[PDB]
Image (cartoon, each protein chain N blue to C red):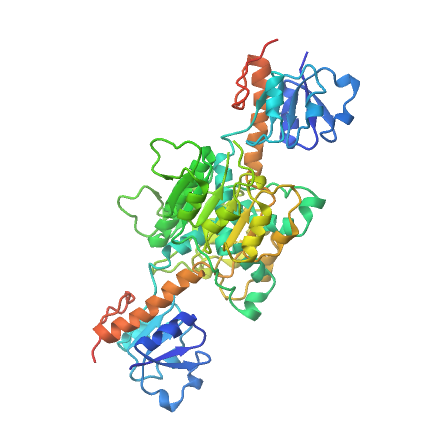
Length: 316
Length: 317
């Protein structure tokens, strides 16, 4: 019979629309083991956006595959899935250009204060008060340091080159044939650049700390489009308050959808609710890749975009 | 020390640097009625915005009008040229900045980043969940540049790196360019889904972006105006947005700035900026420097740095 695919919690409707091509669908209102009933013993696969708790993942003896919606899969315990022989797929490549677009957008918005300028116009202030204040910052003359690279980092770099900015990067191992300036230390890169873009596609927990920010300097701008936990929140707030850095743009946070109240108060900070890939067309392509992974697995025994930790083939 | 009139508001950097070579004369507004008898000896003007002809013609010794900005519509250049008055503007030093703003506006129009930010700041991420998915994207789009120039090229250069095709429409095509030329605007609009209005040249484009150009652009069509407000038929744009004839618009310029038509403020798929193209501290400082440097160059060497095309003049003492 049609394999049974569990979808816990909210997911893009396009996933649900396309699952019935090959599958029977099982929904639970939230990603919670307590919602699992006895008749779900025959679940073979999971399609999920966001957190997949280990107790839910391990409630299914026939589970073969976790199709993760998103290029990041921190919400899936990949080590535990790998240990149980469960293949894990993600959604790379189909969102790369979109995410890079958002990152440039965030950066331009952080530097030039375009959303505030728009707000100023919409509130009637252009007429009565005159011109929106001049943005203290600009992309002109800036040097960018990429913390992490990957296909997304390359895409961002490619865009930034066309803006006439120098590109540096920091990764554990350098890359051959690139033409960006490599830096074996983060702090050293931060010393050499005024704009730090956190991508981090290894542990980087609190890597962007008080010393990295201090090194970045008083014209320094931090853009986080990677992992919220990579940035030391308390250190960022202090640095913004003291003018140790000049500004920041953040698309990710430690405890989404909550955003620290202190960050909301700064006039030189741009904040987005994790919209990196959040267009209809890109989220549809991601939805298609989730489903196509499942279809490919169950029909050919080979997934399309398995994660690096699970290069598996189906046995049945 | 030549006397330089500065009428109305101007970047403080201009006022800081004028005393290097000049005596400065301020009037609170660009108005001939503020002119007193002791200002007869004014030799030059530095001005941002409108320079009314009566003010310009109040000064028999006037040699030079140093315009703050690449656009100089506020100066009657034909009248200045007729009186032998050189006019300078501020090109080049703002090109990359303006192109940056245009890309920003475009990304904001398509991806709704300012609304997403507003949604977060209003507490809606917690209470309601994710910001709605943006109906539009830059992915798969084709861009048509209405007008080109150094700013157009700069925009195109950026857009190529985003993996978008570039078309352009100008009166005469350009040799050795990688872009698809279109002798008609409406034809370009048929071929593309994203129309960026730049129109840097001499020629008239009054209401060129009309109901038919918008209709041609189509129901996935996006209009970005970073050129001249008057180039877009405002009534036609509003109707097209209301009927879903086009999908969205981003505007940095308006017909009667700083006033913005009330109807345009109501649309959820429109991004509006108060003419911030060049409005960074660093670019406005470079513009300020070029205004002053034009004056200094004129009065010290008899040659301006960036005289406008209509006044290729040299100083006679």
